[PDB]
Image 1 (cartoon, rainbow, N blue to C red):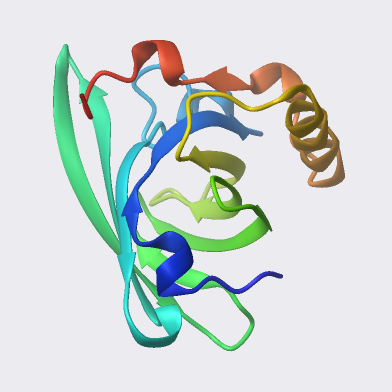
Image 2 (image 1 turned 135 degrees about the vertical axis):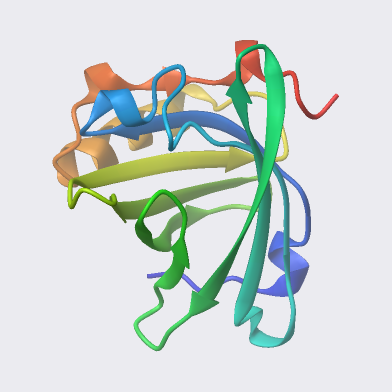
Amino acid sequence: NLDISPSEVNGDWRTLYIVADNVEKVAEGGSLRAYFQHMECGDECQELKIIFNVKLDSECQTHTVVGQKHEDGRYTTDYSGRNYFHVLKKTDDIIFFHNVNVDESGKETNVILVAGKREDLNKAQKQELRKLAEEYNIPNENTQHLVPTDTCNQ
């Protein structure tokens, strides 16, 4: 996979799209429907702090996770079970993350989350997202566009 540096990641980010093979996890009220707000890491990006909101009732419930980087490039963190995440694609203003969540009940969910410093993907990036989901055995019909309900950063 692709490494990230503090200079690349530090700052505000938002979630544009999430797609997952267990749709309940990323649809409204899902445990993994994370509206990014900010990322920050230090030296070598060993310790990656991600601040995000989930919507709970009508309100913003803010969360922070700290991912720990490992030699294989994955970060781990606890959140609604155990997560293993890494970078599948990156540009200066868009990151595609792949996450595997193993929930407390043992259910495994594969996720692609698109984080951005802008509000939209272009058409090429949308097709790339679809191709990646296929490659990762994730149904594209589960795709969630978060922009229209992202109200916790403004």
